[PDB]
Image (cartoon, rainbow, N blue to C red):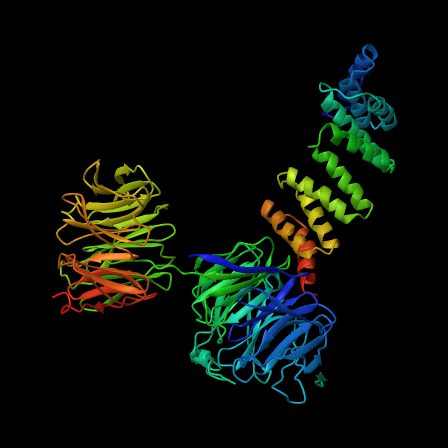
Amino acid sequence: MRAVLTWRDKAEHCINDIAFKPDGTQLILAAGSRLLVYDTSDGTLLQPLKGHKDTVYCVAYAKDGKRFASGSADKSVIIWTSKLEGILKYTHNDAIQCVSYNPITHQLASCSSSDFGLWSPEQKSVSKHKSSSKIICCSWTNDGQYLALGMFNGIISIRNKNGEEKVKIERPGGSLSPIWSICWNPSSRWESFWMNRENXXXXXXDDNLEERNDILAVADWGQKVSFYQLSGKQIGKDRALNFDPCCISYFTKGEYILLGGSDKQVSLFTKDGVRLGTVGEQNSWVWTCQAKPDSNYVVVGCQDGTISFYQLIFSTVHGLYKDRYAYRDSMTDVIVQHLITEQKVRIKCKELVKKIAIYRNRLAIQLPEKILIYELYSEDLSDMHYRVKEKIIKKFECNLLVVCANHIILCQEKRLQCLSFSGVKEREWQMESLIRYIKVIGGPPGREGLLVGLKNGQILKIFVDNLFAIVLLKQATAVRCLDMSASRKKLAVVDENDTCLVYDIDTKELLFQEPNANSVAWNTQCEDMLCFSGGGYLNIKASTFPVHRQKLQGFVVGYNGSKIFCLHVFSISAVEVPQSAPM
Amino acid sequence: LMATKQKSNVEQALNTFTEIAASEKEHIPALLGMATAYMILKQTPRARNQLKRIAKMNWNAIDAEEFEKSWLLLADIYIQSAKYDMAEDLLKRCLRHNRSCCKAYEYMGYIMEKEQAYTDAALNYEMAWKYSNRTNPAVGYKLAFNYLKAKRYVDSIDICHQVLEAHPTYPKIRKDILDKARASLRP
């Protein structure tokens, strides 16, 4: 997990709520006593919109992208066109808290201290409907049919689109645990509704709920988060915290959660409420964390007036062996794919998955606080029945991880450790420079060769049953990537200047080189043939002859028979070789 | 013998201190003895002059702690008299010889709160909170309460968490500071 600050700004005042245009082109911020309009690309502030008298406690923006609602301490609500003019003013009973447009009908809600004011577009009246309590936060059901309200009294209650109240839940403790934000999960058929478009006055004055599929994220100042159905039933258990949370929030996908608060950061979670990481940490309280439409960007607002725009990068985690691509799905599962039979198996963890490695009959997975060893139960090469062999409850720091027949191999930042299954260390090796790359190159069970590449450009072979590391070669630049041919006679190396170099190992001599490479593999059966990717091309080379070039983006992970296992930005693609051409 | 507060022990202590002071009229540890024994004996007017006597002298590194103690005890007696200006002078003179003194700041923060300077009181209470290693929950309360009155409700709630962290079940703070700061937070 990685997050990058794309741009930053600081307002004159505190920032209370955030709205995005549905195409993601503009960001609107309820800062102090004005609305601020921002470009999401680079944070240029286009205009301070002037209409309100007092504190703009929130803003929200309708799914058609024509109109947005903003609410004030001066009791007003204003409906702004996307032409940035405030065509229909309104004036509520007291100060506004949260406002929220309906996903389907564009019907608005506007919450206040006792009273919540529903209306549907350009009708002549508003349902100023009454509440037991201060109405802190509001969210429409994903199909648009219920508005759910959270109360300072520690109750969540569910109201239909007409304003009748249908369901209640109390957090045990009541007003001890104020509900400061709630959110319905976006994950249903309606998310593509309004995803197909290419197009100042005053306004005066439900059964079988267990079969309704929606799920509600609740963040309460008892310092707990929990998920709930429209039936009022709690899902699982309260995911405890050590802070006052705010603005529990989701990406467009409905699968990852953002969680801001008095932890002064934006924490990231699964839809099961398991922690996955940390978006940028902050000088002051976080009030707001809004994911950008259609994309992995995030925007944050804090008590000190800082706005921060982050890109989340979600790196790739995988390993291949000969023909078994194992890779990270969600951020908690490994999908292991038999590339000949096209079978898949899912193994579910209960944490983040940080590292994966695979070898004949052995799979290994590293989580934040344990490492898992998995075993195929049969010697059948078509088997997929992985069982957990052993589970090492120990925390590790690593740069790289690999697995062998009886051992886990850990690369710490200049040091290689061999650990038994069951965690007892066997042997260790100390390099003359920082390790940049490692691969297992096969062997008999328990004497396996490892192939190692260093930042100084030295290349080593290390046998897991031996205390001394064997120099194969040294190079003028760092090893970026590294592979051995089917017989173990030949080496391919990527030199960290984006070139591939190819060597004889038995004589320690360069055969040939190529001026554009990023990843490389030998054909696993047909020696004297290899493949690499670089600069937007796939490149197949046979036996010192010219190289076949065709357009591709993605990277070569392996090469078997007539197929090259290229990896696209999320999934394996299995390109086929023109055998007729090298022939 | 003073610290027992048993009257015969405190009178014996006063007598040894006055005997030493009669042999050595500038002996600060004995003069602080006289003042402290007289305070325990409720002879506060006799303590007052025997501290003024010390307060006129130049400081030195050997008597430094008894100087710093004597100025603080005299500053307390000046707060009983309500002539806070001489207490503030003694507290600041104490800090000029030793900037670490938590009791010099804690008395000064109380004067700033009496003067309705809730911000400067919060500055003194922040030093006293910090240099208590957050083990003074009474300053914890005062710091949160002064942030509440300064219209700094988030900062008040920060400290109400830090007090409950420092001491679970600590009385008063949850209802009065924490829930009134929460109740203001969106008005």
Q: Is residue B84 left or right of residue B125?
A: right
Q: Please name whichever residue, B65 or A494, is drawn nearer the observer in this view of the structure.
A: A494
* Towards the viewer: A332 or B16: A332
Residue A534 locus on image (x, y percent)? 30, 60
Q: Is residue A89 above or below residue A279?
A: below
Residue A295 point in image, percent of width and height: 46, 69
Residue at 49% over, 78% down? A142
Give the image location of residue A293, x and y in percent: 49, 72
The quarter of the image holding the C terminus of chain A is bottom left
The structure residue drawn at horizontal position 70% and vertical position 80%, both measured from the top left corner, is: A90
Q: Nearer the viewer, residue A469 or A221?
A: A469
Name the side, left or right, on which A527 lies relative to A459: left
Residue extending furthest toward the front: A546
Residue A318 horizontal/vertical position (percent)? 30, 58
**Is residue B169 in view?**
no
- Report which quarter residue B107 is drawn in: top right
